Amino acid sequence: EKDFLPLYFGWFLTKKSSETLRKAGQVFLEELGNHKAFKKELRHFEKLELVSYFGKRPPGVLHCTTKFCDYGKAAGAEEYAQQEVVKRSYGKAFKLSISALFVTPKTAGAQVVLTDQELQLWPSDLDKPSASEGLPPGSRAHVTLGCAADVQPVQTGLDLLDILQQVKGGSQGEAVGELPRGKLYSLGKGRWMLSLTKKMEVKAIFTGYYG
Ligand SMILES: Nc1ncnc2c1ncn2[C@@H]1O[C@H](CO)[C@@H](O)[C@H]1OP(=O)(O)S
Ligand SMILES: [Cl-]
């Protein structure tokens, strides 16, 4: 008999923070979908309700996933789960810093900027890691807000990596506009980023989800 691991580890936002971020995300999607610059790109295909477009949303509490384990069937699962830092941090409260919200034609999410301590909990063996894309470790860290109907797991992280590639190289450009919470950037190809004037800090508990 082998101990059967979680579906995935991550930081699970407290009820309060989760609700707070969920609303922020919804307002962002509502505001963005109504923004002149977005509609203009959109009509470059009327008005699209982004909340409906990104219809597959996390049903339970929002979270920032570290290692997907699939109960042990995922590669590197047992190795990740038996890490000292993971055991020590299990059930521990953290604050996750959210610096931006983004959308693409596939996903809507929040960019997480992990601390070095929290970075110790970040998987060392992701299938498509930041390092493979010239970005610092843990840059893929995120809270998914919503996904298009046929968008599979993990896409949100990949999408963030791609967006962070656009800002790194400089493709950020001038803000095309501004929403109450910050400056809005068009990265082209349906990619949009709201750079928060004030970083959002969410309380979350690091633990394992079993489904
Ligand atoms: N390879 C993967 N397969 C499934 N989920 C993954 C994988 N990698 C990371 N995840 C994450 O595990 C959670 C539940 O699936 C989700 O949060 C996945 O990432 P998300 O961007 O939120 S869709
Ligand atoms: Cl990464």
Image (cartoon, rainbow, N blue to C red):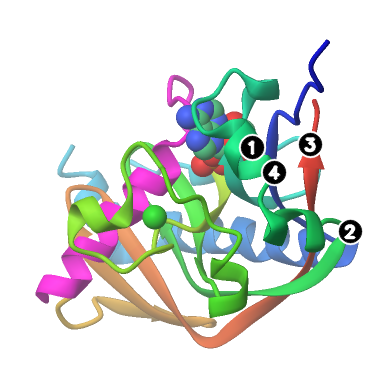
Taken as a whole, is the magenta stretch helix, strand or loop?
Answer: helix
Comes first in the chain, label 4 or label 1: 1
Please tell me whether residue 173 is drawn above or below residue 147 in the rendered image. below
Q: Position of residue 137 (x, y in %)?
A: 37, 64
Can you name the residue that lies furthest to the top here?
Answer: 1
Residue 169: say if magenta. yes
Alpha-carbon span between mark 3 and mark 2: 16 Å
Comes first in the chain, label 2 or label 1: 2
What segment carries the magenta color? 148-171
Residue 90 visible from this viewpoint? yes
Residue at x 71% of width, y 57% of height: 84
Q: Amino acid at mark 2?
A: Lys
Q: Bin the neighbour count of mark 4 within 10 Å (Cα to Cα): few under 14, some 14-19, many 20 and up.
A: few
Residue at x 24% of width, y 76% of height: 176
Q: Which mark is residue 209?
A: 3
Residue at x 88% of width, y 58% of height: 91
On the picture, is 106 further left or further right than 147?
A: left
Alpha-carbon span between mark 2 and mark 1: 16 Å
Q: Bin the neighbour count of mark 1 within 10 Å (Cα to Cα): few under 14, some 14-19, many 20 and up.
A: some
Comes first in the chain, label 3 or label 4: 4
- In front: 104, or 28? 104
* Label 3 CB less than 8 angstroms from ligand 1: yes
Alpha-carbon span between mark 3 and mark 4: 16 Å
* Residue under label 1: 57
Q: Which mark is residue 82?
A: 4
Please tell me whether residue 178 is drawn above or below residue 3 in the rendered image. below
Q: Label 4's element?
A: loop
Q: Amino acid at mark 3?
A: Tyr
Please tell me whether residue 56 is drawn above or below residue 205 in the rendered image. above
Q: Which mark is residue 15?
A: 2
Comes first in the chain, label 3 or label 2: 2
